Image 1 (cartoon, rainbow, N blue to C red):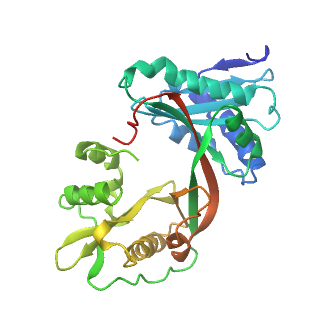
Image 2 (spheres, rainbow, N blue to C red; image 1 turned 180 degrees about the vertical axis):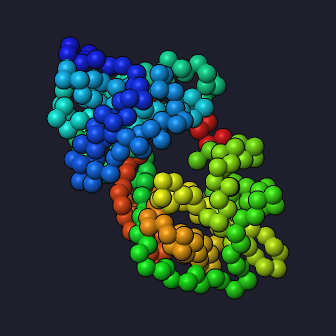
Length: 315
């Protein structure tokens, strides 16, 4: 069911400006500043197939009423990012997007191993009660908190205090590739990636090694920790900071972060952000606030099981 006057259609790159504004109107209601730009939309469209992987609900006045796009992992877990313009709420439109995403994976579901359980998931701003209820109404249930940490560097960060016997090593291309990959797959191991997969995903970011830091034990010459930063559009993003198990509790993550911040700062990057998972109600690790960061926004991950089976998302 959709209101008569409303047309759903695949987005075209010329919709980038219209859609940016839809997100802006949405992020405004949640209490966020309207950061959104068509420039970002065009960039986040770099990966996806516009025809198949996104939908645009066009309003009678020719303006974008609602929009969603999907991230797909091995067809066992579908992430869905929806928005409905704050004027159009309570029209059945947010419900429509939800089922669109559900029907998306259901139509493709045969490409998943048959025993694999199939899930769809949404990341909801903790603040908007409207979408919080729509999830529960639709059977989507709270799984985990995701915290977006941010830091503005207008002033030089503190100098890292490195634990005895560990120091910073800037990633050296042509040398440190395999070793860094092993430390990342261990410290963290989200899906396990093979080495070639990891290589292709990082190919861009490894052309800027200044921002890939390794905590390295001096005696062994072994990577005990990593912080791999990147720079996009004059903003920093840190994908993963982490320490291999035998080296935890030495304050290595804090040193890694403080060091990465120094590189960004003396590079002139004003804002760095990253993202951290936390069990519902625990809050982010004291690590991040101690590194000078602060909470930008909090999302609650909502998940629903489309088909029963063993959990393959992590294997």
